[PDB]
Image (tube, coloured by chain):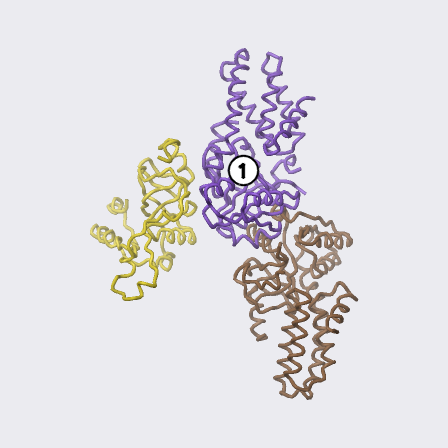
Chain colours: A yellow, B purple, C brown
Amino acid sequence: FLKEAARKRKFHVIVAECAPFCQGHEMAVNLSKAGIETTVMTDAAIFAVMSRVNKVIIGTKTILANGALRAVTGTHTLALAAKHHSTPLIVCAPMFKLSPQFPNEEDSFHKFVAPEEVLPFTEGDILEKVSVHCPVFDYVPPELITLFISNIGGNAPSYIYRLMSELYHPDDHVL
Amino acid sequence: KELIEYFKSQMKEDPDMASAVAAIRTLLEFLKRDKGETIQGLRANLTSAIETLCGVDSSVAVSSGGELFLRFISLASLEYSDYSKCKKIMIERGELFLRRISLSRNKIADLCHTFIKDGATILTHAYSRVVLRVLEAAVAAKKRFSVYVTESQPDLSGKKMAKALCHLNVPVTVVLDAAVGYIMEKADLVIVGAEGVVENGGIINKIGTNQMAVCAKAQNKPFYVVAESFKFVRLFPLNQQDVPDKFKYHPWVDYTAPSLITLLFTDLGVLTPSAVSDELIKLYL
Amino acid sequence: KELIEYFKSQMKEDPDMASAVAAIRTLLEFLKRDKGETIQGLRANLTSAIETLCGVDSSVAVSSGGELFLRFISLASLEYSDYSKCKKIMIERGELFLRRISLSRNKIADLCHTFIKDGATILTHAYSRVVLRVLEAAVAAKKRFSVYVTESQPDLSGKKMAKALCHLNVPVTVVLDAAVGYIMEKADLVIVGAEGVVENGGIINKIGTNQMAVCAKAQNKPFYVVAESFKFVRLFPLNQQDVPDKFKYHPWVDYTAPSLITLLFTDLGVLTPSAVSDELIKLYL
């Protein structure tokens, strides 16, 4: 979505890396390879830099039933900052990323991986006392989202329920 | 007459049962009495009965059930424009509709009881059979939680709700009507029943519900609502004054905007504040 | 003893008068009884009396008045470190302080009654002498307005306020404690009394005040507060739980954040929620 418009428009892209798995560096490099004037930064400076930002475009892992998302860790704070500054937050996700479930569940929402990425094993004896948690994903409510760009055109989160009714059958929700 | 008496009889064998379901049962039972074979005579006689019933019981649910019955008869009229086999097919469809509406409460409980977690605090305003069923199914699911009920000063029904909840071995607690803001921070979610669902998504509930929703919005507290499908009404109040005065009568009801509601648990499924408008548009009531 | 009896006597000749002013009068009157000529004996005997008085009357105003009296004695102690002429000068200064605190109510009314316009609707929660004086001065200024008072379910004092207001030939109206959100749109401003002003600017008032302030914030309604200067207390509650339990005791009081308050009408002048912190810092109480 970003590199398709760089051939006819010129803009500035800010990329916030992910603390557990710094995957934003690859995206920043791939974008700079096309001449888009990209920048890389940490999550701690999200709100500090989100006063000069004009738009936000992100990707999700799955779309829930009430229009909320299961995105990588750090997207909830991004949506909060967007809502504080009243900036539109666009979500580019195909139709196969749409799940027919509401935030029913509890605790098993996020995928927890080994704490090696957050705190290394070479710390010392403090690892027996310190409790480390490494959630990969997080929950983003629908109220902080503005638009959903899909293969069938953009739509509002308040219409995602209809897409659910259009995609899946109510008896196959539990599977 | 017989309409008043039959309504009160159905209300009295089981107190539990709501007024709108009893009204629909009375309307269908009086449908067997109909002798006229013209469609406007059936329409006017039944519409007269629904208005009289609504006069007897000033509630939004009765009017909603009456509007739904007339819309269902209008669909069964667009069947063939017959009123020769139409009355028969209509009676069968109505019986099916009544049996289907009977299971609404169980469906709502089985679908809403999953949003309650162990160790969480719930905040309810007034007594409601739907929230009671949800809580009974949650405690039936090997869950433990605490509940806070508002005393509901207009009529002391919150104490009845607390008694019925404490009877189920749950640590219930009654708070003052003016203390809804003091205990809002000690609540994880809010679940209340709705007397009637408006066109946009808001709810018409007891006088002490909109202020609680406002406090929930002020503290990012999930405000859930549980209501059946026969409570959908084609109203669109813009404020507390646009609500019809016949439903309020110290008013006895208020309107809550959909922006303060998180989700809706109905027999048709778990819905958002906007999906009800789609449903109402599909019915063309 | 004599402290309890003197407090109750001063409370009983005039009911109108608040508890903190009566407590300050009793403390100054018992100051004449003091025979010890050491400063810690005077300090401890008087501090014992203030704690006993606070035990008898569970209110934030009494504690505020006691804290202010001890701070004023500490200043009169930093006078010379004498306790030879110090007791005398202290008694004179205390008499002056009492006469000055007597006019606080009139000053607050004359300063707050100007913010009420002709034809406006006012919303009050519970009975308060300060809001009553403000309304009496406004109607004394050839003004006409309507008032809505909450019944205050914990103790039926809202009805007393409505009676005292209707006695002044004003179209008062009593609403339910759960109806604060239904009549919020029909109110132009909100004026209520404060039992105690916290360090940041919030107020400790009846249990049904924070929810009203929240509704006022949700509808951009001016929320004014009227309180005296002897009600300033060095507390900083972060939520409804940080408030001391001795003041709450179904709690009888709640805390309101300063972000929901528009202005403050005190005997020191019309102030904003932040100027009270400056005043408290200047006193070093």
Residue A151 shows up from this direction: yes
Q: What residue does disc 1 label?
A: B130
User: Residue B124 versus residue B244: which sits nearer the camera?
Assistant: B124
Mark 1: secondary structure: helix
Q: Position of residue B110 (x, y in %)?
A: 46, 37
Percent coordinates x, y for residue C106 in the rendering: 72, 66
Q: What chain letter is assigned to the residue under label 1?
A: B
Q: Is residue B279 left or right of residue A20?
A: right
Q: Amino acid at mark 1?
A: Val
Identified at 55% across, 53% down, the residue is B183
The relative height of residue B40 versus residue C156 in the rendered view (above or below) is: above
Q: Residue furthest right?
A: C13
| Residue C120 visible in the picture | no
Q: Quadrant of residue B55?
A: top right
Q: Quadrant of the N terminus of chain B?
A: top right
Image-based side of A49 in relation to C168, left or right: left
Whether B12 is drawn above or below B264: the answer is above
* Of C273 and B180, the residue lying toward us: B180
Give percent across and percent down for residue C151: 68, 51
Q: Position of residue A66 (x, y in %)?
A: 42, 41
| Residue ID at (47%, 31%) | B279
Name the one closer to the observer, A145 or A125. Answer: A125
Q: Total of numbered circles in the picture?
A: 1
Q: Is residue A166 left or right of residue C78?
A: left
Classify C192 as above or below B282: below
Could you classify mark 1 by the number of other residues whose Cα lies within 10 Å: few (under 14), some (14-19), or many (20 or more)?
many
